Length: 552
DNA sequence: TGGGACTTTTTGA
DNA sequence: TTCAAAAAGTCCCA
Ligand SMILES: CC(C)N(CCCNC(=O)Nc1ccc(C(C)(C)C)cc1)C[C@H]1O[C@@H](n2cc(Br)c3c(N)ncnc32)[C@H](O)[C@@H]1O
Ligand SMILES: [K+]
Ligand SMILES: [K+]
Image (cartoon, rainbow, N blue to C red):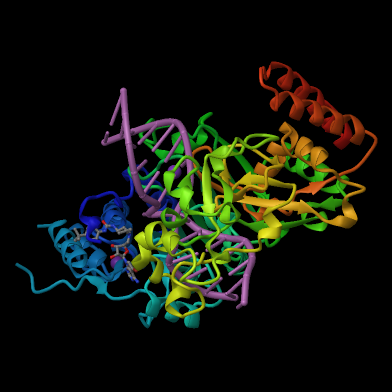
């Protein structure tokens, strides 16, 4: 790694100032002149140095009141520095050099005496035996997903942090849990993390832990905005407390324009109160396992559709992920590749990518998949294995199932069942800016970037493929799905079965007209001299029908 | 260097 | 035996 020295992970100063102010704005320094403020991912001290400055001003502005109320010899301006570093600032980080630099910076904040002990711990914050809780906790924890996390460390997290970390969870789930655990009664925590846990299936346990253990004061959701320059992550700020209150309401600040520069205003509060953000309140007591954080109009819209629709896609359809070859370059070839003359056409499948999926129809495929699982003997079709697949034999053997012997070196890692793909079905891209559900007539295969489903036999008399793609591609359903969809990056939502199959659908008197409009759209889209203007008009008419059906 | 087009296979269950 | 989730995405260009 050692990319931390570049500065891409440095938290923007406006974010840091907001989080520190959020935690310390209303601290009664007279009542408690010994607040413990902690950052368990302090790094070089982006947060902790600002904490020092805020504390110094807070002590200096009340120095005489402190001198009068308490030991008058102890409370002096010249003593403020020492008192802060002795009793107030706490930092933990696993990088020794970061701790050393932070110690030097904190010591140089004053610039002889005997010695000042700075409470900086070089350790694994997730393993440290914390000997006391803290008044305030701030910072930016590390984010590490299931692929990039070390195996032994992952075993430790699975054993010890099972309440929030399991399956495809992230390391910052555990940091959330640790922060909550060591926060004092009545304390306040404020952190910047990825936003994905708000909606992701992996974050269900983490959402339950937060909801049941702290009061969430505020969620700032930047959606797909690029808060961290040259980092592909979407960020949010969470502020929570352990204060005894009867109010269970959350301030949600949801950005409206993802193309804004965060330095537009001198402070984050100006941006939050501006027209660039929307604000609304969510009753924490009404949160289910999912957190539906939308304004009143969207909530009314969502509840109307949920109540009106008696079926869901999961009820009526069978869903599946695409082929996972485990090495696409060894099995995927251009349809015009001369090497395909070496492969019998019985082994060749049409192969599409997510970009080949439009609304209602799939682009003509330009790639072929060698379904190598049907190769019986290694001696037969030896040219295919020697001249096409074997070119990547080493990387093929590094696959998990090849090393365990479950798969031959030339087989597909996850070849699924051919019969699921070789039928009329609906396909949609796994990540997209809008609903794009297409009817596949061409027995197209795909990788995991395209998901498929087909209608169950018992529901074929009630739902047709043409009707489903009509309502699923409508503006109503685009908005409806995005209400709870998992926002990933700028103009990209996840379209994964764990949320797509929860989409609810309806049947009523408009079924025939909606289906007919969808058929007209498909017929136009499949023409030779295509002009989509009529398609847009038909789509507008269909959207009007769907809005009439759902009463919105 | 910042923004847009596009998306693999490793992995736990 | 074999499913599906996971962006500190990845990569290119003006
Ligand atoms: C990095 C980021 C994604 N993350 C936050 C931004 C840190 N900010 C910063 O400014 N870091 C930094 C910068 C420069 C250096 C030098 C000395 C090499 C120049 C060191 C740290 C990760 C930070 O959290 C620390 N970390 C990682 C783990 Br994993 C961990 C842990 N288990 N316990 C405690 N601290 C931990 C990590 O040590 C890390 O600090
Ligand atoms: K006194
Ligand atoms: K982003």
